[PDB]
Length: 276
Ligand SMILES: Cc1ccc([C@H](C)Nc2nc3cc(F)ccc3o2)cc1NC(=O)c1cnc2ccccn12
Image: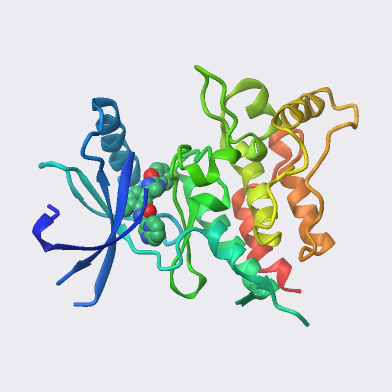
């Protein structure tokens, strides 16, 4: 529950808490195991226990799945699926769009449809992710995608978060205008972050959203959405993205939260309409 002795620690996969590739004899069975740092504070331990609880809610092919736990003894462990290809941002970065390692346009749509399906599931639970982005997705065998949430602290993605002393850490470049101005999050702001995530996929993660603008400019842009005088600025159409699919992204960035398409409609478009 889970038998900790059945675990065989093999390699470190990354870094609050280390993640390790482990083997389970059942024989070539691989899992990911997250362990609390030896010097974790009482606050870190509490957060870890809550992550376990939140994660235990989530049961979908395109969401990270809690396979097991070791909490009745120290140190605390969380066990998930091992996703061979690591995070989606690093994965796409190592690929180029097929001409005429490579990835094809239809494969990009399949990646995006899987994210939409995972988010469709979350919406059914009335669960708001709050930090959807390619950096929070993992890639397994055969371009299979699982949405996760690594938190906001990793050095690699430091530049994706706006930090003011004593305030919540904010992924402003993925955030709906109402999130920036009022600091609250909904399924409708998850849709907006999905539009930005889809922009990243079609960019093959080559540039930060609004990359040529400062943090302060991105925040003032939310103000311009609010005022609605036609001065707001949008992510440009990626090279690999045709106009029809771009117009979908634009609906995700509608000023009015109710005008943003539900994830059920987004999934339909990506899995069906976008095929023609
Ligand atoms: C073992 C574990 C525990 C926890 C988590 C994730 C980060 N925790 C998490 N997601 C959430 C999604 C929500 F909606 C809400 C809360 C969430 O909390 C992930 C993992 N697994 C890996 O990180 C992993 C697997 N395969 C590889 C390959 C390379 C690198 C890393 N990995």
